[PDB]
Image: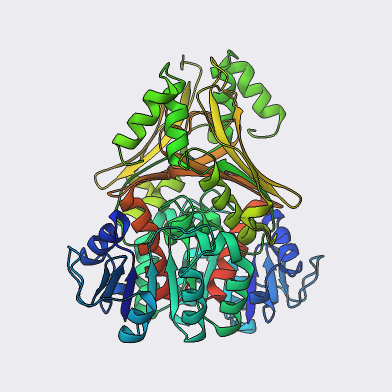
Length: 299
Length: 300
């Protein structure tokens, strides 16, 4: 089974490493046939990217004819391209998709998944929400139950800053430190909004796009002497993201640092899952998990 | 596909109800060919149980020839019978098994699963641990990562009592309240840690892999000599135990209160925790229904 890996920053490199650690006999037959970035097309599997050809993901797709596309490229929220048209072409050609790239899903969920459903093509997208902590994939093992609402912390950067602020640290100092660690556009709540959009689509069955979500982020001026979290919320009627003061009896109170959490409420039960929501290995692991599930015929 | 439903107490009745709610198209062709209880064998799927024949689960099995056995019968921790023999006979007949009955798995996991793997038979057992809250099935979507250790709160009754004790209630008063809400009866058997030990045994077997039986678990319960304390069930490659321990405010198990259950799974890559409600007939039946759907998807 031949993969085309689209994107190769830290997540793409971590994925490649996971793949070479031979973690499941389900992946024995899996190779990376090509890697494409801004800088061109490498038609080999190497730790370091050196282009072999000039050209874009469409040229690479035609040349390689992969069985699976793994998209770990940067989210383009303006219009989702080129990943959006890439997924459509992959689906048309019977090529399964594994992705950590939120934009196409947050902009065009119903169109993409309807098209995939019709063609029997599979999409793994665990990596788009809460990295390697089952979220999408948790819902896969909650069959025959209707999700009524979801509430969570879905962004590592802002959780990390809000956690430090609660320890007496300044916004500015906290922001600095988040960046130093590998975490305007970073704190305005948008990332969480895209994530709740995807969850709302998948779990609630509410066909919404990032345009339907009321969100706002964090800043220097938030209330002092209160533990604040950036809460993402969706039910059958509304989808929003906003910073709220949280009380000690709230399950989300001690979800700190880059930890993320999702409270899923169904007809049968309310559950909560929590785990890291940032870190390239974690993101790469969400994609690896999808790849193994795909090989098991379980997406 | 034809099910044989072994047990028709609250879990079985809930299961039959969930099946009839048209919850997934995967269950379109699934019918219950028969229900068996202590009162005999009903060869029909009706809400109200009325036996058509006298006889035990083995007679029903031979008569119906089910594709799947769904075991929601009461756990017999003395020796796991008759469920243990039933599973072996089913496995050897190529009949898949969905179970909420902990006993055979707590006593003879490696024997049962080795046999199933040798025969290519599938076993759904999500319902045995944290009922409807993915636990077993959570691990099914955490592939390619070795589980190093697991820790959890696996028993609602003791957690409820300890939750009250942390808020300043005496052990005696907390137990009374537990008894008032029917969580404990002699409450001796409800608070001795055995239920948690059974569950952690199953989880250790499945997630960590080393053959362990309930006999290998060092477990103790709660009592009036405890001073935020939680009854922690723990397993790694070396050991499996249950004991009351103090938990820090930063610990993800800290607010797992009331009758809630939770499980923390630690791998090389990461630690994750899931929390849910822990016990109830509908919840347990939903664990079995989830297993059935995954079986129909061919994902067990």
